[PDB]
Amino acid sequence: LFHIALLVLFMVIIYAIIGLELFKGKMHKTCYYIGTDIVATVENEKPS
Amino acid sequence: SRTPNKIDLYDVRRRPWYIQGAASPKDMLILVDVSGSVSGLTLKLIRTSV
Amino acid sequence: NLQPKPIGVGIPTINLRKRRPNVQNPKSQEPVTLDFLDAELENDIKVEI
Amino acid sequence: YVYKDGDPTQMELRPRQWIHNDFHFDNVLSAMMSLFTVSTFEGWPQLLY
Amino acid sequence: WKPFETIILLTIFANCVALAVYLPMPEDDNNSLNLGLEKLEYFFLTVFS
Amino acid sequence: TAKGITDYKKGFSFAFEQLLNYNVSRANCNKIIMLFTDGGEERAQEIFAKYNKDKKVRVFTFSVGQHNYDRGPIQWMACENKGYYYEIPSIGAIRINTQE
Ligand SMILES: [Ca+2]
């Protein structure tokens, strides 16, 4: 399985780097109630 | 309750007039467990009960 | 000297950064317990009285 | 009352309701749909709990 | 010969049954039974040493 | 801040001593001690024998939060002392058990 290990390892690395550049630091803004430091979200929703 | 957006959380039992005639005055002493196991959700609850 | 406003304790500190705008916290329930030696200027000849 | 972020000071009012789980074991056609989903490994821990 | 291979085996089995009855308590608490287990740990050790 | 072990013996010795000051100004009426805790493995039978052999003091034990610690000893303490037992798992449960 050595030859497949190499492949999978290099796949993750490549995608990891592409991911890096592509969306590095683009996920730091969320909706907030005005003035407060609380996150605004519906019921069964995850902060996004 | 819901016709404005402020909602009353008034309980008769809680009231001071109700309490003085409920019972006799008292020397209490709140004893709290602060061992490691309490830390967590439970520790949070105790500070609000006392 | 006694007044309708509740008797206050401490310097009031509320954090504006952590009050979400529409939830309605409790207002007050304390009794208005002003003392005679706090409604008037204290003497030693008034603590006797 | 419900408490946002478990804050004994920040609560909203909600009506009470008797709810039924979407996947149950009431009859044999229900328990079975439940088992198919537990067999696809999708959401089986919820059912388990 | 025959049972020293088995005595030691059951010893390595009882220690397993012991690592598992243990109860992890937070912030450093501890039930009186975990203490009993630590005490038994020394025996287990001297048998493997 | 919570850390360390749990000794239900130094907690009720300190409580009884506090209850017996009699130098200070006091209510001198109902004498009661209430403990907030989650689970207890020790009933502390010895402290209650002497400090309150005749049951002058009343003990109320509160078990709080969602947890697996044993509640039998705490219930026993409450029963022994003519107090009561109250659970509190939740914030909405605080308001009717701390007045009850
Ligand atoms: Ca404990």
Image (cartoon, rainbow, N blue to C red):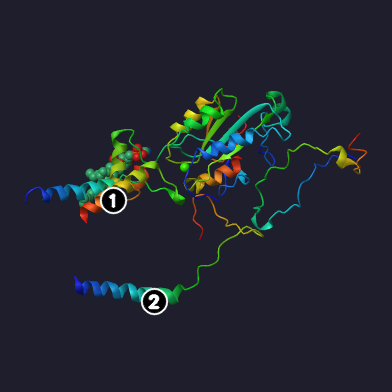
Q: Nearer the viewer, residue D25 or A12?
A: A12
Q: As drawn, which residue projects farthest toward the top?
A: F54
Percent of width and height locating residue D11: 61, 44
- Whole-number angstrom distance, CA of label 1 to CA of label 2: 51 Å
Residue A13 spot, x, y in % from top left: 34, 75
Q: Is residue A26 above or below residue F80?
A: below
- The reply to whether the C-beta atoms of the residues labelled 1 and 2 are less than 8 Å apart is no
Q: Nearer the viewer, mark 1 or mark 2?
A: 1
Residue A17 - label:
2
**Callout 2: chain:** A
* Residue indicated by mark 1: E42
> Subunit of mark 1?
E
**Type of the residue with mark 1:** Tyr
Quadrant where the C terminus of chain F sits is top right
Residue type highlighted by circle 2: Ile
On screen, residue B25 versus residue F59, left or right, reads right
Q: Is residue F89 visible?
A: no
Helix, strand or loop for disc 2: helix
